[PDB]
Length: 463
Image (tube, rainbow, N blue to C red):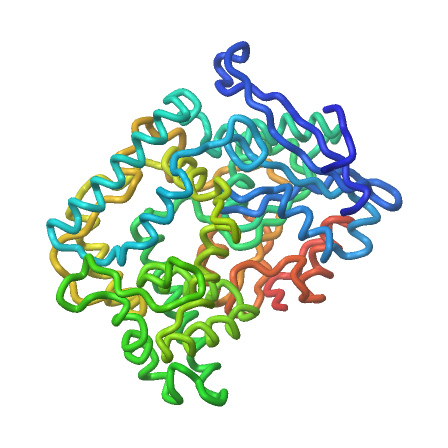
C-alpha cells in the first residue's frame, strides 16, 4: 500500500487491491480504502478496527475512535480503519437505491400487513433486488460476504506489515472477528469484540431477542423519563407503550393504513410513522440520545416531528442535502450472503405474531395473519456462510464485551460468543449498544491492559 496524507491527525490514506473472487485471483479486482494514525511511541503494531453494520465505514469510525483513544494505546499502536469490500470508499461500492428511492420508502407508514399490504411490500423488495443486480452484477454480490471480508483482513494484516492481527470489532464487526479467528487463528495477536453477534444463532430467534432488547431499552428509557419533569410519555411507565402509541398512531390514517398523515416539520417531508419508529430505535442505541427522543416525543404532542425525523436521518445516513451514503444498500447485500434466508412464509408469519407481543412499542394495530418475507428471501445469489458454533481451537484468548441491556446485540449473545471462543467475558452494566473507547475509564483500562500486556479480565469482571 502506497500511503498519502488524507483529504484531522497525522493520518495517512491508501488503497489495497484484493480479488473479487478468491478462486479466480486473476479476475475482477476490488480496491479497499484504508486510514492510518501512526503510533506516538514504541510501536507494537497496528490496531485495526471495525464499527459493524454491516455497511458502516471503518475509516469514518477510526476518525471518531481517534478522539477517544486512550493515551497508552495511541502510543503503542497505529490506529487503522478500513472500508470493507462494497462499502463507502472501497471500489466498487454497493448501490441499489437512489436518494429518491430511499425517501419514497420512508414516506410510507409501512404498517399494512393485509394481503394487499404484503404484496405491495414484496413488490418494492423485488424492484430493489433487481436494482441491486442491475447496478452491481451478480458476481460482485456473490462475494461481498464476511467470509471474504475475513480473507481481505489477512491481506490487510500483511500489507500493514504485522505478523499477527490486533483487532477491535463492534457489533457486526464481531462476526468479521470470529470469521477471521476461524480461518487464521494462528494470525491473531489479540482480539476485542464489543456487542456480540453469535454466528450459531437461529436468525428468527435472534430477531426476536433483538425485539425484546429494544422493548426492554424502551422500558428503561421511559422509566428514566418518568422521573423527569414533563415526561412526554407520562409519569407512569407501566402506561408508556400506550401513551407512545397515542403519539405515533395518528401519523397513520385510521381508515386506511397505507395513508401517511405525517407530523409537521420544517423539512418538506414531514414525519411518517415509519420514520417515527426508526428515530425511536436510533435513540435507544444510547442514553446519550434519550434527551433527543424526549424532545422528539414532546414535539409530537404539538403535532411536530423535527427531532424524530433527524434521528431517523442519523439512522438512515441521509445528510442535510438529502444524499445517502451506501450503508443501507451495503447492509442488505452483505446480510443476505452471510446466511440462508428465511423463506418459509409460515415462520415469518409466526415471528410477526410473536414480535407484536414482545415489542408492542414497535407494533401497530393487531396481528393480521400475514407478514412479508424479508429482502433476503428474494436474493439472487446464495449464502457464502451459515449458522455454526464458532470453532477455533488454537485461538489466543480474546475479550468479549457485552452490555447487560444492549438492545441491538443482547447480553446473552456475548456470553455465548465468549463460550464458543473460550475467551474472557467482560460485562458492562448499562442500556446501550457497545461501550469500548466511549468514555468508561474502567472498560478502557481492562482493554488497554489486554491490548498491550495480554492480560485478560478476571472471571466475572464487571465495569
